[PDB]
Length: 119
Length: 48
Length: 49
Ligand SMILES: *[C@@H]1O[C@H](CO)[C@@H](O)[C@H](O)[C@H]1NC(C)=O
Image (cartoon, rainbow over all chains, first blue to last red; front, side, top):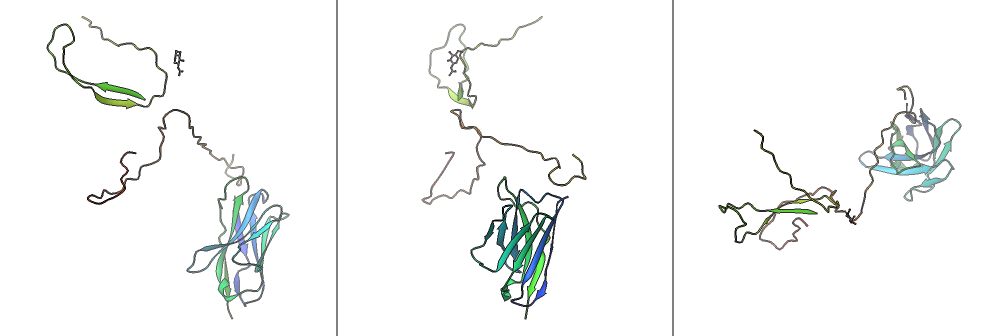
């Protein structure tokens, strides 16, 4: 059945890069658009990025140049490159999936990965 | 809209309609939305 | 349709609601959230339309 799993979380120095992976199992990776969302402890959810089958990446206007969304369809995976980490990016990250031939319901969700930045 | 107005009157006249005034209260409005051009009363037989 | 199939081959039940706005009276309306009644004050009243 449908399953999203994530990896790449941990406790890292600020300014060091990260590569968060979202592997999809059970459904064909095409015809769906993939989202990266984060939520901070004590704060609500904040949307990070979108990527489509074409390769069009759309980012939040609030945060610019910090992340890079990279889709791969040979092995049905999604990658996030995070650069110039600040102290405020301690958060739980989620991988989300919307169907391209409907409204923007995010359907099933990832379990989440923890990113803790410290000095 | 099908408006049904009705009034019950206690009379004791034998043959014709009594002469008087009685305004009919609205009883029920029906949202039917259909064409009606003909009607027929329904009676009851007495069997013995 | 089998339970071992993944998402996309699973049976989906679909109900499609279509609305009609013909010259017939609008019998179908939304719910009517009645609030509490306040007296002796200049208020905007809406009683049954
Ligand atoms: C109602 O029925 C009569 C007889 O069948 C017809 O002449 C008339 O045009 C109808 N009216 C409408 C609005 O359909």
